[PDB]
Image (tube, coloured by chain):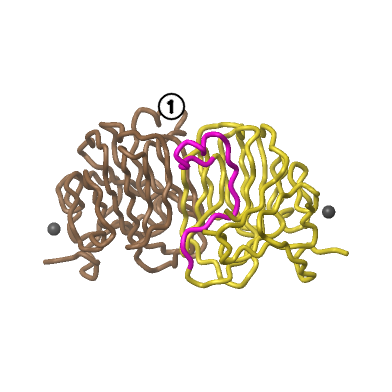
Chain colours: A yellow, B brown
Amino acid sequence: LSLKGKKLDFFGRGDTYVSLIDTIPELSRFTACIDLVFMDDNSRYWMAFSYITNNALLGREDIDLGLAGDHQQLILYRLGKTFSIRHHLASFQWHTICLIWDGVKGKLELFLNKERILEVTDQPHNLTPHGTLFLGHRSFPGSLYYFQLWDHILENEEFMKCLDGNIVSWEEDVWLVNKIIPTVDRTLRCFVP
Amino acid sequence: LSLKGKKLDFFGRGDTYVSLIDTIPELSRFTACIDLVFMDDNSRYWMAFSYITNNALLGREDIDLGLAGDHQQLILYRLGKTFSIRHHLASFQWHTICLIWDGVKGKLELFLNKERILEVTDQPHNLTPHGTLFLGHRSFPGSLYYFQLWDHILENEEFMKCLDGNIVSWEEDVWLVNKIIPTVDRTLRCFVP
Ligand SMILES: [Mg+2]
Ligand SMILES: [Mg+2]
């Protein structure tokens, strides 16, 4: 299924997920962005996207890459390590969160719209290949939109220019939906007839 | 020299530093806190405290532990890795910043007063022993006060209770001053006649 012009209303929907049909190749550098909106003020732990490999099916404890959080925190997973920062994100407003991984330098950065909020150093490492990307997956407390993944480092000034990822693009017919109906919203940030 | 009842006015003083006379032992877990106040609104890169070992005298690029920042960021150094977070700290107000290192779990946390702002995961590792602790060292753009280091993990609720570190304590006669005159200020948070 293509998600062009559509968002994913995950709020309250515990047995729902969306997954990318294509496995993802080995990436030394990449940028991954998603748009999200929280539809409740005080939430529990949540996941927006996760990249799951065989590492995870052992005890369900190790995620190669993911964006998660709680009511006061954003949480990044990298190769089983976690990095958590305090956030004050408003509910009922769309936010764009982008992650940059420079596997050559071993640098992981998190942005809110054009502004960097976290830079972490870890082992230089590529992205482990052939995992599966999951969205929303208890369920994300709101809506998700416009996931993109590029095999290179985007500059801040490009994050909001409504580009399509060259590895994963929302608009492509690459998505598997489980018990969720994507919905059209012509007010969405990058919507174009 | 003892720093009891005194602060260190480093603002604008480029060739000044304070160092701890005692070398620090190997620590598997520790808490380190300092009070700081910025005396200019828009600042450049600064360091509040650093723990320097022989790793650093090679090209002056690797710091085993340090707290640094710029006008919009707080920066933690651990064994040469950096972790940077966006901050919005007000000038002309005292802030208490505490770091917790759990070398058993490989967990490094940063707090502003009682509130956690960063949790990072890294290699489980102890603190490298016998380095030298430096304060202020171009110079820190304001004043520093009440550095403490304990060989155990303090809970949030204790950070502001004006305890003395059991490894390093501000009030002990353990400090070497270079070209700075510590100043008494009876309004300081933990001052007691
Ligand atoms: Mg396009
Ligand atoms: Mg005392």
Residue at the (67%, 34%) spot, across then down: A27
Q: Is residue A24 left or right of residue B187?
A: right
Classed neighbour count for the residue bearing mark 1: other residues with Cα under 10 Å, few (<14), some (14–19), many (≥20): few
Q: Which residue is at the front of the view, B171 or B82?
A: B82
- Relative vertical location of residue B14 with respect to residue B184 in this rendering, above or below: above
The amino acid type found where label 1 is placed reads Leu
Where residue B29 sits: x, y (%)?
A: 27, 41
**Percent of width and height locating residue B184:** 22, 63
Q: Which residues are magenta?
A: A43-63
**Image quadrant in which the C terminus of chain B is located:** bottom left
Residue at position x 31%, y 59% in the image: B35
Is-magenta flag for residue B101? Answer: no
* Quarter of image, ligand 1: bottom right
> Relative to B189, is B137 above or below?
above
> Is residue B79 rendered to the left or right of residue A94?
left
Measured as percent of width and height from the top left, residue A100 is found at 63, 45
| Left or right of residue B128, residue A138 in this image | right
Please state the chain letter of the residue tagged with numbered disc 1 in the rendered image.
B
Q: Residue B103 is drawn in which quadrant?
A: top left
Q: Which residue is mark 1?
A: B58
Q: What residue is rendered at 56% in x and 70% in y?
A: A90
Give the overall secondary structure of the magenta segment.
loop
Q: Tell me: is circle 1 under 8 Å from ligand 2.
A: no
Left or right of B177 in this view: A166: right
